[PDB]
Image: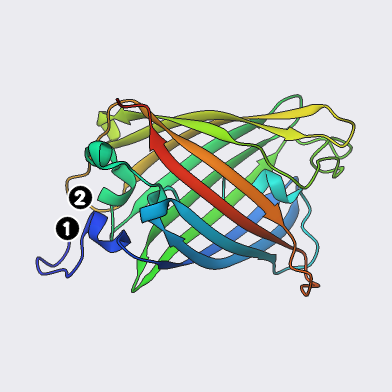
Amino acid sequence: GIDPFTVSKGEELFTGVVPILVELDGDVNGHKFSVSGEGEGDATYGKLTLKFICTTGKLPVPWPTLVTTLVQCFSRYPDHMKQHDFFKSAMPEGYVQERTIFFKDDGNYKTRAEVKFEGDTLVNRIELKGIDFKEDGNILGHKLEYNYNSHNVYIMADKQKNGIKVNFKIRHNIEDGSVQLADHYQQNTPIGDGPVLLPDNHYLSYQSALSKDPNEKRDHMVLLEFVTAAGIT
């Protein structure tokens, strides 16, 4: 565990506005890229405000496909559900979050991230690997709209990993009015060896809005997001 004294533990670290730093290195069908992100989260309200920049030039996949990859510790857990907040309970030492995201009739992303505090800053460091994509598909062919939908994210305990398993589906809007499904399988494990909250089944409700910074000339994405735990009582 940590130093007992460690001024703040788990939930205590998220009572106020916390700065966020996101770092992603990716490789999709050999198209290599990096993204950095910065902003803050206010878990009391489930609120995230973040700006992401492709630091290597043009992003070789659509921004919306990276949203789920690019800090569920910022979810607003109702008081009556506080005993189910795995994500906060793993802090400050943090957790590893792993996903496989299947893009229907296209390739897959496999992601590994470590989410933890570095001082006052909540850091999400991510490696993304994408294979089996079509060069002319909705992803490498850039055929997705720059927008996002609301979703529910379904959580259950994985007692064998002292962690959780998570799953959900994202539907990205295609420019022709159709829909590109991205099925998400996820697992999270604590980095530290201390006790974590292993939750009953529940879900997080998401709202996400994407926009552009009128003064930003690099390839980028502005994200406003609200996340709320629900499903128990």
Instruction: State the image coordinates of residue 24 (x, y, percent, origin top left).
Output: 59, 59
Q: Is any part of residue 2 visible from this angle?
A: yes
Label 2, on which residue?
193
- Residues under numbered marks 2 and 1 in contact, where contact means CB atoms less than 8 Å apart: yes
State the residue in front, 51 or 70: 51
State the residue in front, 27 or 190: 190
- Indicate left or right for 119 with 68 as reference: left
The answer for how far apart the CA atoms under marks 2 and 1 are is 6 Å
Instruction: State the image coordinates of residue 90 (x, y, percent, origin top left).
Output: 28, 51
Q: Which quadrant of the figure contains the C terminus?
A: top left
Residue drawn where x is 70% and y is 69% of the image: 55
Disc 2: CA contacts within 10 A as few (<14), some (14-19) or many (>=20): few
- Indicate left or right for 80 with 167 as reference: left
Q: Amino acid at mark 1?
A: Gly
Disc 1: CA contacts within 10 A as few (<14), some (14-19) or many (>=20): few
State the residue in front, 227 or 122: 227
Instruction: State the image coordinates of residue 59 (x, y, percent, origin top left).
Output: 77, 57
SS at circle 2: loop
Mark sitting on residue 1: 1
Mark sitting on residue 109: none
Instruction: State the image coordinates of residue 126 (x, y, percent, origin top left).
Output: 53, 55
Q: Is any part of residue 67 visible from this angle?
A: no
Q: Amino acid at mark 2?
A: Asp
State the residue in front, 82 or 89: 82
